Image (tube, rainbow, N blue to C red; front, side):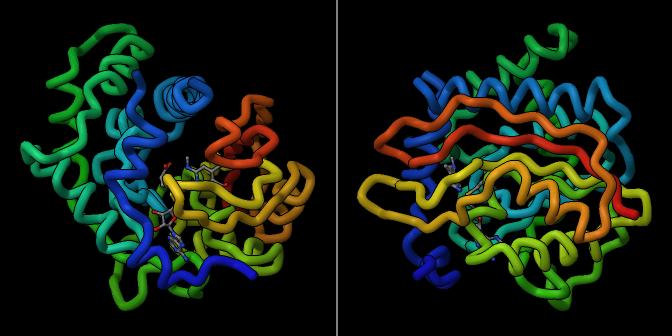
Length: 254
Ligand SMILES: Nc1ncnc2c1ncn2[C@@H]1O[C@H](CSCC[C@H](N)C(=O)O)[C@@H](O)[C@H]1O
Ligand SMILES: CNc1cc(C)c(C(N)=O)c[n+]1C
């Protein structure tokens, strides 16, 4: 009774997803602001840095990487959907048909103290992203046959509830992402709480409805130690999903 992963290849419209959730012109904008403040805190205020960050289930979005590119030499973006990766690549290659992230970029520049302007920030992100890869979090080797050095950080925003049909798969996915991480490496997860679906227009997608206790327990079971865990009550618009807030966590691999 859960969305099949092949539905992501064919029925997840990347430009419609961006239009629906990331236009930043709403509950969606309030959530985006909070996600950005947390990412800024992690990568710029806390010591989350290194040579390599792997972003898991990036979809067609870059917002989750804007603060990260200040702290990581290389960012690898990954997703199950080739269509999502193509939409991402349109922005990376600064193509005229690319999504306009400029209000989000400006917001991050403001958070970071206006040290740089939008164009410099976008260029820094474009230079950090060297690889755009296929991933499947449900597999023991999420990146398949593709070899990568162990990462300093694995980040995943709004992916794991959508990718995991049940709690045992969710715990296994956390172990699978851990295989990409160096010992003592950072795991950064942000996702919806108690959400059983989300919509992109008329297209419905399943979500695993987890509470904060189940998320914490799965992260400890998967071999991590939690540094901090935050719950926000703000939910997406009623037309989009049925979540009861969002969580953010930073953990280290044992
Ligand atoms: N098994 C799986 N492994 C990896 N990615 C998967 C997956 N099942 C679904 N996904 C991806 O999970 C994403 C959910 S959308 C979240 C996109 C983005 N990180 C954001 O913050 O908005 C989609 O891009 C979808 O292709
Ligand atoms: C904004 N993107 C969202 C939003 C929600 C609420 C869910 C979910 N897990 O229900 C998944 N995605 C990918």
